[PDB]
Structure formats: C-alpha cells, structure tokens
Image (cartoon, coloured by chain):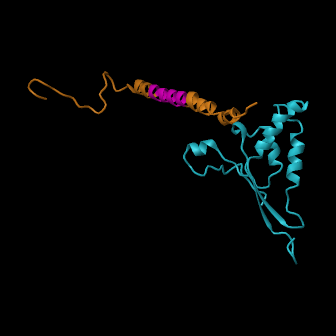
Chain colours: A cyan, B orange
Amino acid sequence: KDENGKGRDVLLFVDNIYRYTLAGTEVSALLGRMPSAVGYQPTLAEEMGVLQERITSTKSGSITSIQAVYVPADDLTDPSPATTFAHLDATVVLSRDIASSGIYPAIDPLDSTSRQ
Amino acid sequence: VQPHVVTVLADTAIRADNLDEAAILEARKNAEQLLANQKSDLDSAAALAALAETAAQLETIRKIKNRAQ
C-alpha cells in the first residue's frame, strides 16, 4: 500500500500459460500420474484454477492482467481453452483464415466477447 | 406477283381448306404451354429443391474439422 493510500494500478501480462499446461502434461506420466482423456494431467483443471484465483483485483488495489493464449492445433474444443473461458472475462480470439485474407489484425468479431 | 416468282408474306399462313383450323391452333397453344409447364417444373423441381438440399449442413462439417479429437 502507498502511504496514506493503497496499492497502485497493476499491469500484468501472461505469455502462453499454455506452456505451463504443457509442462504439467510433460511431468504427469513421470509423476506416477494417469492420462486425462487426451493425455493431460487430470489435475490440470484444479491447478489452472489455483493459478487464476491468486490473480484478482481485490478490495485492496487493482490488478490488470493480460493473457497470451496459444491454441493447440487452432482448436477450441481442446480441454484447456474450454477451461480457460471459465476464467476470462475479456475473451479475444484470433483466426487463421482472416490472416489468410491478409487482414492484420485477424481477430474474429463473433466469439471474442466481453461481459462489460 | 412477278412474271416468274410469287411470295406470300401472310400473317397466319396455314395449309388448310376451310376456316376451321381452330381445332388445331388451340392444340398448338396447348403443346407450347405444356412444354412451358415442363420447363417450369423441371427447372424448379430438380434444381431449386437440389439447390436447397446441397446447401444443407456445410458449415456444420466445416467447424468440426479443427476438432483434434
């Protein structure tokens, strides 16, 4: 907290949490663990939630977070993005075909949405 | 009429003997309208039906490509 005040506006920037997910996949089998429906660690959902929950603007201070979301094989129905939507108030999605049209940027109007 | 050639530019020129070909001109008109009916049916019934049919669920399949599962 600032003297005679609180914390400040916090700028946060995530770079492919998918990498963290991928590492969890990398380790699970060696951990004596089982293989999810695709091969992920079963614990992926809970660990993602644990990760996300320590990320919030509270009564104390404001924390602004930006997330890089790589999409494996460009698929939404993958478990990890699906879980991810349950975490993101601000959702922005890219497309390959839009870039195939040369439009830079290539954000899809539809799926990217906001509860604001 | 010319000393050797005659041309007859008739509006309705019909090989006939009596002014009673009404029984055959209507037949001609019915043939034409029936073939028009065939046109309107086969153009519509074949294509327009198939036009809708071939465009049924294309995007439904296009989205389920990128399914890696």
The percent coordinates of residue A99 (x first, y second) are 58, 45
Figure label count:
0
Left or right of A12 in this view: B35: left
The percent coordinates of residue A17 (x first, y second) are 77, 46
- Seen at 31% across and 31% down, the residue is B12
Residue A103 within the magenta-colored segment of the rendering: no
Image quadrant where residue A100 sits? top right
Question: Compared to A89, does A47 lie above or below?
Answer: above
Quarter of the picture holding the C terminus of chain A: bottom right
Tell me if residue A81 can be seen.
no
Quarter of the picture holding the N terminus of chain A: bottom right
- Seen at 56% across and 30% down, the residue is B47
The percent coordinates of residue A90 (x first, y second) are 76, 55
Q: In the image shown, does A55 or B21 lie closer to the viewer?
A: A55
Q: In the image shown, does A62 or A85 lie closer to the viewer?
A: A62
Prevailing secondary structure class for the magenta stretch in the rendered image = helix
Question: Compared to A28, does A6 lie above or below?
Answer: below
Stretch in magenta: B30-43
Left or right of A92 in this view: A83: right
Tell me if residue A2 can be seen.
yes
As drawn, the residue found furthest toward the bottom would be: A4
- Seen at 66% across and 49% down, the residue is A108
As drawn, the residue found furthest toward the left would be: B3
